[PDB]
Amino acid sequence: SGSWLRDIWDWICEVLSDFKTWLKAKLMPQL
Image (cartoon, rainbow, N blue to C red; front, side):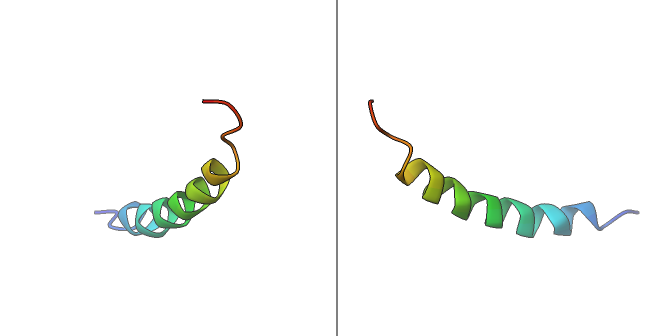
């Protein structure tokens, strides 16, 4: 089995989620 891509998504989604909050926090001029 691969058993490797699952580990990559574990840290990729975590690091990506943190940046999403940082970007969304300064990307809401008009809502």
